[PDB]
């Protein structure tokens, strides 16, 4: 059908058809008279996965022979989404399978909708890990993703009476065709116990043992025949566990609860024991696996030449004292050599600046659970602080500021401080975030070791986030500039010479229109909701957090509503305002914001005077599969965090690549995005970081804004008095009180500029030719935000390895 | 190699070889350089199972088209053992796979040792269910086994310092190639709640829901291309279960614990709530599945013409009030018609007479867990007792004796009484057991409804228990009489005309010798134990129970030891005495008996004066796979339960078929076995049932025996004084006290006759030609004890369906 989806050869199509029927019969034990759509999906899935195995076996064989330096990417989250289409795309099988299934009398797109998301992450950090794995395979690096196989991923979100309900994401219910259990490689992980000191050093004894069972999932590169591995650990009780009889067997559950569920509280650090166990479990199992592989290459001096470990935030920070423990206690290296090896091996990526998100584990927890690790941490702290003392003699306050141990009511370990001390590199995830690290939160560490601090601006994979989710746009671009850009996204610059091309303009706008019709249909079909596809699609999708300022968007929405009611017979650009995202189950304010959004929808969507000039829809259960649908259909991307709070953002980049214009603050990656496209091609508004700092100095007084902006006052009055909650008039009192008296994120301060800027957006949209021309200049300059570029920078500047675009033999 | 194992055709062998390699690559994701023996087993397993699927799909298709009457065999236990060899045997693939694996450079027998036992049963009742499924498929009946998929089966037994230790049987750890999950057919099961009465009848409301997920396993007939289904239910939490957040997800475990583990307490009824839940779970899910299938045939008058439900003991007795509940409350049939349908549908098999084993559920349990079922049971009881009153007017004691409700401290439901009331047939499992039911324990019910009471003497499958475990014996028989006997075991009578055939005599004795060498080797290899293979193999294998009198065997063993020590230079027939079996974890006396056996071994096996004339070995972890090894190697089968206590026994029959002579009491099936072979060809001793009754009348005084038998006194003195426990002299005080003052099973009363009879055994064994001739007359008359015969009797006399030896088209 379309070019970039590969060849549908006669030989291939005939082969796919017969293997499909083979799987239906032998694998699924069905025949065509009993088979459901789900059976058909599984048959296709097995037919496709057959094509990975030879490539997977010989890639891993290749790494054994050539013995390159290995990259280990440690994360507690991998937000993978669906795998079928991604695999077809990366193997050039998409048109062939489409044809084969067509001739079998099936619609492949319908089968694709049956696959569950692998929802093993919360948001940006988890999705970043998934994009990175894809780029690492595409760039031919010998890379492994290591994490936990959660039985339950991020909860499915139901909206009930306007309110979020959570339900278990039982994603493994029907089986996972993309994993291979490897029970033969099961490893023991130890907990509790005590430390004994002997003549021959320390020994960790009387431990409880939990088994770590690995499951491998393939990660195919883009048409280079490379298939890397993601290894996820599952928790298993040992067989003499608790071993009246019946109870002992039932208590095996306690051990296995370690990998049962993903923590969804991305807002607020909770020092929960189960979470600590999860963090140690992935680290202990992974490091044994690493050392095993290394020993199959006594000389640990070569360890850093052969191993790189990337720590995705502080969640796997225990890798540092765990590597030390192994090297010192088990291999009997001396401390200094062990430390040298550890530092050269580990690197740390920070993904936030919000204080309440930082991991600070109570000492009494580490004492009971990991007694030997606390001792190692204490020793690291002493030696580190001795280095600080010698560099800044007499600076006693620096010492307490830099300590890994925080004193107070409860003593705590600062895991970020541990990571910086024990890593040769520390990076932020966009240029302004990295500068903020060096200037404010890790200033003392930067002064001590400026060489450690780097930037690696985030990216997204153009395979999933263009080719897969927006084939129409991929095709019209391919027609003009060829297919090479898919794995060299900088080529999109060549599109600049088409900004005045009437045909291209028409094609870009047509692709968008089709995307909007497709999504407007999806809404009616799966959610019985009626939207006008000629309106501007105004979309904000991301986790619900105060810093992300979904509330500022709410304020604009009500402003538009009030202006319509005021001058009903005046013309305004019609909008469909879509907001979506999950709230952490314990985050009251975020749950209230969701309720507000639905409450507004309830008023706005049923007002006859509004007609269909304004619609407000809450997008339920936002997740990778839904992002792949809504992003290609968007016209306006809302990226409106208070400057200084969004470390990078990556959703922003997905919208840019897919032909939406951006309204945003100079925050995170938005800055670099505006820089690449030109500030004239971006709707920038609001305080910069410096203005925020100024405001904090004087003190932020929300009342000032309320007193001087009558349009804002009106909104606040409506909220208080119960205009949006007729039956519970004080329903939103918490929200109003927060905005008026304790708003950490200065919602009111940006209100005027935001509304003004929104007027400029509406103006441009009235001129379709000029809207589309600006869109073209965005797409054309989105090349920098490919994760191939990000990963090539990690490889060269942190891990010390050269990427390669060369094919392995098929 | 050997005939009965089928053809190894050039085309077949080449096909098996390539499918093996296909599976190794695509299914296991290995290549020959990394593959372990386990990988090889799995590749063969997948290669073999491929041959079942077409047969499985068309058998079930056939039953849909022809719509025969369906047999549902309900059991909480299916002791299946291993499946690979059984499948090859039933499909005629054994020689072909042996060849194919040979040419691949593998030993198939070694691969077969890798498969775990499906240990989903305790002993005889569970193994009976497995033999029955095999015969039902072999006889072409449209039959389904329904049960629970336990995550953990019967525990593995470790012997530590002479003592039993239990460890979890994690049989699913590496995956089960013989099952197919069917999540699409998941059904809800309800618990707790309350009953509401409306105008439109009773309604069961406010229930907790647990999901039942079926797993199907094939059951192939012997070379007839029939493949029936065993469906096992697994417990799953519903997705809004408990739905702070983290805990809610972790508590899903509570629902799923229902199918976690098999109860191993075969000795003593424990009214544990979890066990009741298991019993209801299998019943509720199964009956919905049955009704579903029936409705795909309002007219429930045809229900008994289309459905038979066999209840394996009282464990699924809740099927009776559950069928009533559905028919009355949900389909709105009137009580009398519902009852008529239920009775004609259900039949009950009793597997014991021991009072402490009978299920008597406290009313307060059924009240909380199954409030509607208690009401239904009460109503059944009233109507039943009204029938009793009318038949035996004024007999008030009969009324209280026959009631389903037992009064007392705690009111209880007698589940056996429920089963008899609600079934059209009640059978025992051997002729003497069935007579005992009618004369003693169910006398009142027999007087009321004599037509209900039947006998169906147990059997074993000659596929597993001859062809599979003893190919050498199967072959030498096949040479003389052909292969037809394998599915028509009565043909073995033809062997009588060979009792004086010198060649046959020589061949029978040679097969036994090879079996003993093979087992003597297995012992040395896997357990570093040294046995003389020229000795008489004296074997008692079965669960450890007082009624089974492993203690009487212990007494004989010590007698032989004492007689040797007394006259060291006298000749005696050398013996290897092997005893094995698991004890229920809470059964103290049974655990003490195991300790005694090992303790004796410790003394006897290290006495230089004994040499190798006497060895005592405890066979660890007795289970189906071990039975398949030890039974063909046995010379003497010990079947020595107190007369009246072993309902049938089936191990007895396995030994008979495999060329061991039997020493036994006239108990259970032993009677019919002696009757078939001739009492001259059997070593019968001890009290008959009548003698036991007499002894109880006068009162059993153990002291009498102790006073009159000096050889017995000596043994008791040795036990008391600590001869077998030098470091803990009073270790066996419990055992001695039990024997002297509270022996329910009259061990001493049979002592003299037993020892005497054992002398007669030793005498015969000195004359090999005559030993073997008697062996031939046993094998030749073991035809009656085939489960094909047993099942043909159930089919004709209970279920009303005709068996068929006709092939389905391949
Ligand atoms: O879902 C049912 C079960 O299947 C099992 N898979 C087995 S037996 N073969 N896999 C083969 C395989 C082939 C190719 C690939 C891929 F995609 F190319 F990489 C992955 C796996 C899984 O181990 C188990 O966890 C799972 O629950
Ligand atoms: O760099 C990629 C993206 O990273 C994001 N950081 C995220 S998602 N941190 N998650 C923290 C977290 C903490 C605890 C937990 C929990 F619950 F304990 F399991 C889960 C997540 C940035 O906010 C974004 O600007 C950036 O683009
Ligand atoms: O062990 C890995 C997993 O495999 C799954 N099997 C799947 S996907 N195909 N089965 C095909 C099949 C073919 C033939 C037969 C047989 F023997 F002819 F009857 C049985 C099953 C199981 O459903 C799951 O419970 C299990 O854990
Ligand atoms: O007919 C076949 C054989 O059946 C046997 N009966 C057995 S095994 N009953 N099990 C009872 C039992 C009770 C409770 C439990 C438990 F633990 F709650 F789960 C398990 C088993 C007879 O004793 C034998 O003579 C006969 O040959």
Image (tube, coloured by chain):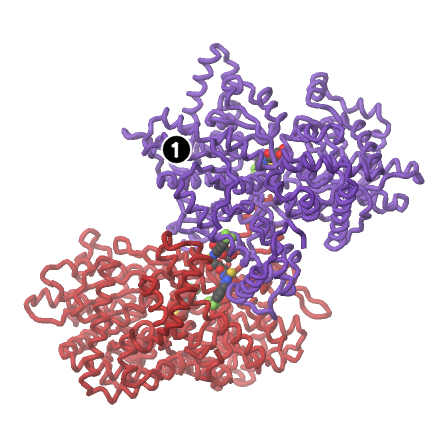
Chain colours: A purple, B red
Position of A267 relative to A117 (above/below) = above
Percent x, y of residue B684: 24, 80
SS class, disc 1: helix
Q: Mark 1 lies on which chain?
A: A
Could you tell me which residue is drawn at 39 percent across and 68 percent down?
Answer: B14
Is residue B306 rendered to the left or right of residue A66?
Answer: right
Is residue A773 rendered to the left or right of residue A213?
Answer: right
Could you tell me which residue is drawn at 23 percent across and 75 percent down?
Answer: B511
Q: Badge 1 is on which residue?
A: A303
Q: Nearer the viewer, residue A361 or A578?
A: A578
Residue farthest along the bottom direction in this orientation: B497
Q: Nearer the viewer, residue B432 or A123?
A: A123
Percent x, y of residue B78: 43, 68
Could you tell me which residue is drawn at 27 percent across and 77 percent down?
Answer: B473
Residue farthest along the right direction in this orientation: A569
Percent x, y of residue A721: 83, 35
Is residue A551 rendered to the left or right of residue B712?
Answer: right
Is residue A244 rendered to the left or right of residue A435?
Answer: left
Residue B340 seen anywhere in this rendered image of the structure: yes
């Amino acid at each position: 059908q379309i070019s970039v989806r590969g060849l549908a050869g006669v030989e291939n199509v005939t082969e796919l058809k017969k293997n499909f029927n083979r799987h239906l019969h032998f694998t699924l034990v069905k025949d065509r008279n009993v088979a459901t759509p789900r059976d058909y999906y599984f048959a296709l899935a097995h037919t496709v996965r057959d094509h990975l195995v030879g490539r997977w076996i010989r890639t891993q064989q290749h790494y054994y022979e050539k013995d390159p330096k290995r990259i280990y990417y440690l994360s507690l989250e991998f937000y993978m989404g669906r795998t079928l289409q991604n695999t077809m795309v990366n193997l050039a099988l998409e048109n062939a399978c489409d044809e084969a299934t067509y001739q079998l009398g099936l619609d492949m797109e319908e089968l694709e909708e049956i696959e569950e998301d692998a929802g093993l992450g919360n948001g940006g950090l988890g999705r970043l890990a998934a994009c990175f794995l894809d780029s690492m395979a595409t760039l031919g690096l010998a890379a492994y993703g290591y994490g936990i196989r959660y039985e339950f991923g991020i909860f499915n979100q139901k909206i009930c009476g306007g309110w979020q309900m959570e339900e278990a994401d039982d994603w493994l219910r029907y089986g996972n065709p993309w994993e291979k259990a490897r029970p033969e490689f099961t490893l023991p992980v130890h907990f509790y116990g005590r430390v004994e000191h002997t003549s021959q050093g320390a020994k960790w004894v009387d431990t409880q043992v939990v088994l770590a069972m690995p499951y491998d999932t393939p990660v195919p590169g883009y048409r280079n025949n490379v298939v890397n591995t993601m290894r996820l650990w599952s928790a298993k009780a040992p067989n003499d566990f608790n071993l009246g009889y019946i109870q002992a067997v039932l208590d095996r559950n306690l051990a296995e609860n370690i990998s049962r569920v993903l923590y969804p509280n991305d807002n607020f650090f909770e020092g929960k024991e189960l979470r600590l166990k999860q963090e140690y479990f992935v680290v202990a199992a992974t490091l044994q696996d690493i050392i095993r592989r290394f020993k199959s290459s006594t000389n640990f001096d070569a360890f850093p030449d052969k191993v790189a470990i990337q720590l995705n935030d502080t969640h796997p920070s225990l890798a540092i004292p765990e590597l030390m423990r192994v090297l010192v206690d088990l291999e009997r290296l001396d401390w200094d050599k062990a430390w040298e090896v550890t530092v050269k091996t580990c690197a740390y990526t920070n993904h936030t600046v919000l204080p309440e998100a930082l991991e600070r584990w109570p000492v009494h927890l580490l004492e009971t659970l990991l007694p030997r690790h606390l001792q190692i941490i204490y020793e690291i702290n002493q030696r580190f602080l001795n280095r600080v003392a010698a560099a800044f003699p007499g600076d006693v306050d620096r010492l307490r500021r830099m300590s890994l141990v925080e004193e107070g009511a409860v003593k705590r370990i600062n895991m970020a401080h541990l990571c910086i001390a024990g890593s040769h590199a520390v990076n932020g995830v966009a240029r302004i975030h990295s500068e903020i690290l060096k200037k404010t939160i890790f200033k003392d560490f930067y002064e001590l070791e400026p060489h450690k601090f780097q930037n690696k601006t985030n990216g997204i994979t153009p395979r999933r986030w263009l080719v897969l989710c927006n084939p129409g746009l991929a095709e019209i671009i391919a027609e003009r500039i060829g297919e090479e850009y898919i794995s060299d996204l900088d080529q999109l610059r060549k599109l600049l010479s088409y900004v005045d091309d009437e045909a291209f303009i028409r094609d870009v706008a047509k692709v968008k229109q089709e995307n909007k019709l497709k999504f407007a249909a999806y809404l009616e079909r799966e959610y019985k909701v009626h939207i006008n596809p000629n309106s501007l699609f105004d979309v904000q999708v991301k986790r619900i957090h105060e810093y992300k300022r979904q509330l500022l968007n709410c304020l604009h929405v009500i402003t538009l509503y009030n202006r319509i009611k005021k001058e009903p017979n005046k013309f305004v650009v019609p909008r469909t305002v879509m907001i979506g995202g999950k709230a952490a189950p314990g985050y009251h304010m975020a749950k209230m914001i969701i309720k507000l959004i639905t409450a507004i929808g309830d008023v706005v969507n049923h007002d006859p005077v509004v007609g269909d000039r304004l619609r407000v829809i809450f997008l339920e259960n936002y997740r990778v599969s839904l992002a792949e649908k809504v992003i290609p259909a968007a016209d306006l991307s809302e990226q409106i965090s208070t400057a200084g709070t969004e470390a990078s953002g990556t959703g922003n980049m997905k919208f840019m690549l897919n032909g939406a214009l951006t309204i945003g603050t100079m925050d995170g990656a938005n800055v670099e995005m505006a820089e690449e496209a030109g500030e004239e091609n971006f709707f920038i508004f609001g305080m910069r970081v410096e203005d925020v700092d100024r405001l904090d100095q004087r003190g932020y007084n929300a009342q000032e804004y309320y007193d001087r902006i009558p349009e804002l006052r009106q909104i606040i009055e409506q909220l208080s008095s119960g205009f949006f909650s007729p039956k519970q008039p004080d329903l939103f009192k918490d929200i109003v009180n927060m905005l008026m008296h304790h708003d950490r994120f200065k919602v009111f301060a940006d209100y005027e500029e935001y509304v003004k800027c929104q007027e400029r957006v509406s103006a441009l949209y009235k001129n379709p030719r000029e809207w589309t021309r600006m869109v073209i200049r965005n797409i054309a300059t989105s090349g920098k935000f490919s994760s191939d570029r990000t990963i090539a920078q990690y490889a060269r500047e942190i891990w010390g390895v050269e990427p390669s675009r060369q094919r392995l033999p098929a």
